[PDB]
Image (cartoon, grey):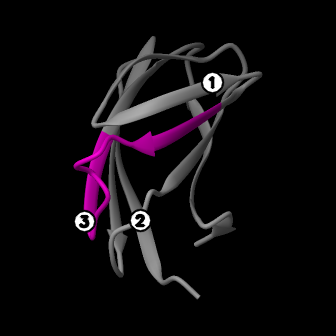
Amino acid sequence: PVSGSLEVKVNDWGSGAEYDVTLNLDGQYDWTVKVKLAPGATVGSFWSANKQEGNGYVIFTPVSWNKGPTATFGFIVNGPQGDKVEEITLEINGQVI
């Protein structure tokens, strides 16, 4: 199985919050990070990744040069006061790390 970890630095300012993510992987992968947004929250911008968004869910994948072993990317979420995100989960090969 693939080993690794996810870390994220959060800076919330009321109407929005910035999430700086760092993936500590045991190699290079075309990883996936799934983000469950809080009610009424939406992604305002992002970097170092491609984004797929649906009903309350966001999926981030790497741009060509950001496959690890230490990948970093980030995004800003706008929404109601309180935590803007409920879950941030790293998956590789369809399996949660």
> Compared to 6, does 1 lie above or below?
below
Numbered disc 3: secondary structure:
strand
Q: Left or right: 34 with respect to 9?
A: right
Q: Left or right: 42 with respect to 23?
A: right
Mark earlier in primary sequence (1, 3): 1
Q: Which residue sits furthest bottom?
A: 1
Q: Which residue is mark 1?
A: 53
**Amino acid on which disc 2 is placed:** Tyr
| Residue nearest the observer in this picture, 75 or 32 | 32
**Amino acid on which disc 3 is placed:** Thr
**Can residue 28 be seen?**
yes
**Can residue 18 be seen?**
no
Q: CA distance from mark 2 to mark 1?
A: 21 Å
Disc number placed over residue 70 in the picture, else none: 3
| Residue nearest the observer in this picture, 62 or 78 | 62
Pinpoint residue 35: horizontal percent, then vertical percent.
60, 40
Q: Which residues are magenta?
A: 58-73
> Compared to 48, does 5 lie above or below?
below
- Residue in the image at 60% along x and 13% along y: 80
Q: Which residue is mark 2?
A: 29
Q: Image quadrant for the C terminus? A: bottom right
Residue 89 falls in image quadrant: bottom right
- Residue in the image at 56% along x and 13% along y: 79
> Compared to 96, does 15 lie above or below?
above
